[PDB]
Structures are given as structure tokens and as C-alpha cells.
Length: 78
Length: 66
Length: 223
Image (cartoon, rainbow over all chains, first blue to last red):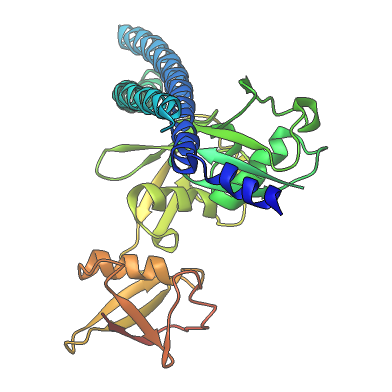
């Protein structure tokens, strides 16, 4: 049973540094993926702002129209 | 004593750290845009209040000139 | 099959789906399991923003696959709640929302329990049963909030120092949120306080109806 010994030896050869490398790669790529996701979050919040600005502009337009109507009805006191 | 694997390990850790810093500044930008949203929403709410006011005014004036 | 959904907040929700499920249905399940409206959800797989009309198989989403959830600050429809103090509250709603749901949103935003709320639209007090569409509550339409000082169900809680305190609750309230009410009124943080009723420890997942705790029932608080 030499191949068993060789198996254990191959598994244990720089095993600690190898496992460290694996875990480290996992952490690294987790961080990078989180970077991508945060960028997506940026995009999303940006979209939200665009929508709010749109609705705010609409509301302001409505305000203008209502002020015009008010001025008109104030004119009609003659 | 497996120095190459150590090399790759150091590289991986460096990349990890850099990625984390980038994450930090990304957090900053996110909070910025969120703040923009909140402010815009505030102004929107004010605008809606003014709309309600002007609507009541129009109703009243229509009640008068009638 | 089951899939996973990863959020920026670290949480990884586990969902039970079929390949023929639409993205819309998946978002509905995320809603049932997290309380987030579908139109405020953005699902990402393979770098693609998933479209609600497409299915999971259309994006080759296999078993044990992982989607990414990005949350939006606003949905497609907002309504405005007007209180007597002037501050115009803004609510993210969908036309399918019942009035109880709206009151739940007002609760999540302002802390005021639904049974202490009184919503009036166009001079008519809104009933908890009907939906927003039922009252023709269109986008940006304004409701009016009337406050109630007390709800329908009160329970009392005794501290280990002999001091008892009242509490406005509902039969659906979990022990966690009861601990939150104790946290607001008295100040005791949820992780330090242990709630005891019927000679047993109260778990943070069980509702008040789970222990069938009726009105005017006294709970014993320890730490």
C-alpha cells in the first residue's frame, strides 16, 4: 500500500498554503463581485432619482398651470 | 518550501484588499445618490403641498366668480 | 427545484421554484418571503437585468443557481398621506394593495400601528378590506390620516422591579416586535429582555396568537 502513503503525502504537501490560497481566492472574488453589485446599486439609485426628478418636474408644471388658472380667476373680478 | 503558492497567495490577498477599498468608495457614491433621491423626494412633497393649496384656491375662486 | 438570491446586506434568501416560473413570480415569492414589492426589486443573473415576462429557463437558471437582488428606493406608484402637522408622507404602493397594507406601510415608516390609523380619501373613511383601486385611488392622490391614541388590544407587561406597563398590540404581533414595543416604551434592548408567559419562554418567531395571548393579559418580563 504505497499509493495510500503517496496519496496522503500529496494531499499534505504544502496543504496549508494551498488551502489558504483557495480561501483567499474565494474572498478576493467575493469582494470583486460585491464591487460589481455596488455599481449596480449605484445605477439603481440613479434611476430612482431620475424618476423622482421626472415626477417633481410634472408637479411643478401642474403648479404653473394652477397658478395661471388662479391669476385668470383673479382677473375675473372686474 | 512551496514559495510559488505563497506568491500567488500574496497576490490574491493584495487584489482582495484593493477590491475592499474600491468597495468603500462605492459605498460613498451610493450614499450620495441616495441623498440626492431623498432631497428630490422632499422637494416633490413640497410641490404636492403647493398643488393642494392652489387646488383649494381654484375651487374657492370658482365658487366666488360663479 | 430551489434557487438562492444574494443581497448586498449579506442575506441569501432560499426560494422554491420551477423552471417555468416567470421572473415576476420569483419577485412575488421574494415579496412573500421578505416583504419587498416586486417593482422595487431588481434581479440580476449572468449580468442581465431579468425581465418579469421571461421565465427562469429563458436565462438558463438551473438548480442551486444564484441570482442577485438590487433594491430600489421607489416603485412605480406613490401616494401621499397628509397628517394634521403638515408633513406630507410619501408611500410606495401597488394598486393591488389593501388599506391594511397601506396602514402597514405607514407603520413601517412612522411606527404607528394600523389599528390606530384612520385613513380618509375624498371625504370617505377607507375600509381595511377594499384595495386602493376600489376607491379609485390613483397615482399621487392624497389620503388624510387621523390618529388614534389607543388600539383595539392592550396587554400589560411586568418588570422584575414590580413596575407594569401597558402596550398596544395585535394578535399577529410576533414576540420580537412586542420586545420592540417594550424597547420603545421602557428602553430595554430586545436581546437583553426575556419574555415569559404561561410559565414558558416566548420565542421571537411566534405571534401573540400562537400563544393565544388574549387582551388585558399580563406578561412577565425578565432579563
